[PDB]
Image (cartoon, rainbow over all chains, first blue to last red; front, side, top):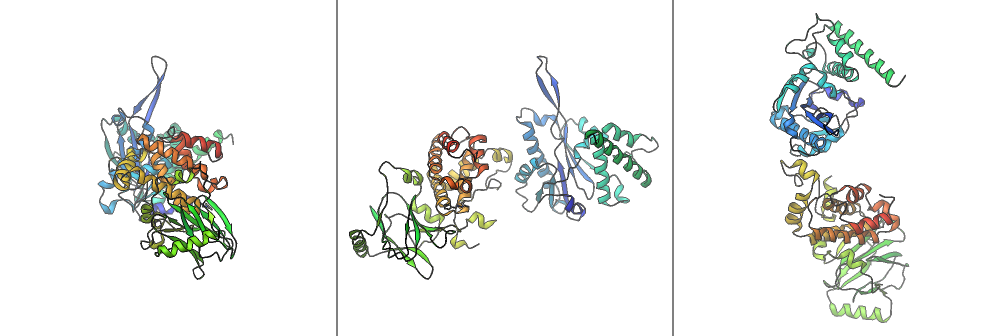
Length: 237
Length: 300
Ligand SMILES: O=C(N/N=C/c1cccs1)C1CC1
């Protein structure tokens, strides 16, 4: 059924699975026209498709050309997502195809089920988890490749860098979700916490800075603090 | 002007004949139903006074043979049978009519209700949905499951309705996923109408049979079939104008006939709300929308 706090360890077992987040597929700026009406301008988007066990990120860049001459784009965006995920599964060797795909938004269930009818043994699941994958475009190197794309493109990343050398997938996913939650709640504050000390750099082949185990504990503490403060101001609590 | 005689009525029972019903007492000198209109299928149905929770009956057409009812004390039910000796049968009906121990099919001259509910229903199509080839009549009851329900366990006693599944390869053309899921016109027109039913009369005949089994027996799988066939039309942007006009008449009479107190268990809120207010055909079913809004505004 639905993925929740009760069945959380299932994310780190040996059954291949992917999270799919469609939040950043269809992106617009809203603006006034010369006549004082409102119009949208699409900007490049991305599908966020993540193996939470390995950290492998399949970032399908959605070029604005996709939307030209199409109607009902928020509806089309869910179907285009399902089409691209389906195309990705078909492109993988059988032994690498996922057993389950977990969609971060319930509106993706029907489009993905319909595109995956050919794969009756792949389970399409919702989740009760409120995952902060919308904040993916706060990761500077991911934002860069999306906004520079001139055509449809798939780019592969490891969102955990080399962390799995030192920590389990459970711990790596917990750190990822804490960093993205912080970036979603107060992007400027989160980015300052990550990039303030200039001695700690981001390797060319990495997304996040090269923190020692001790520095990750401090960073993780600074992120939890940022999130609780912002909760207090929100709810006047 | 046909007759279905009864050997006897040994157990207290409610007897339905089409949309009508009457009570018979244990060992009441009741010997059947006369003046049954030729030209239509009919259904004779039973609920025992001692078991209100179960309903069973027989679809038949008096043009296909001489049929009678006889209670079986072993299987504990009223059974339909064919009498192959026409002279013996005429001799039996004449005697019971002379002694006036038969109820008359109580049709009002003005009243087209039964024609209106059975317009496209044909015995040869009933016998393909309900398979018992050695009989010319078809048994249905409350508990019989559909082929569709069975796939999600005795095939011999199932309702073989045409399987409709909006999330199936049959329903969705490779490369037309979003188009075919949001506009079911291809599934309705090419797969079902051209492909399986051959024409809209056969499609309507199955829709009308499914409703009647849902109403008369409380058959849950029949109710699911009726709603799926309405939803397939309502969710299609491209339907022939004659089909929409006929569907509106069909549903009007079904909603008019439904018992007011069963509106809650016989009508699916989601399907009706979608069909009348959201679907491509939301403005196409004037007669149906008016009777539903005036009779069951709570459902909507
Ligand atoms: O669940 C049901 N119960 N209906 C009972 C009835 C009793 C007599 C006629 S209908 C309907 C199939 C959906």
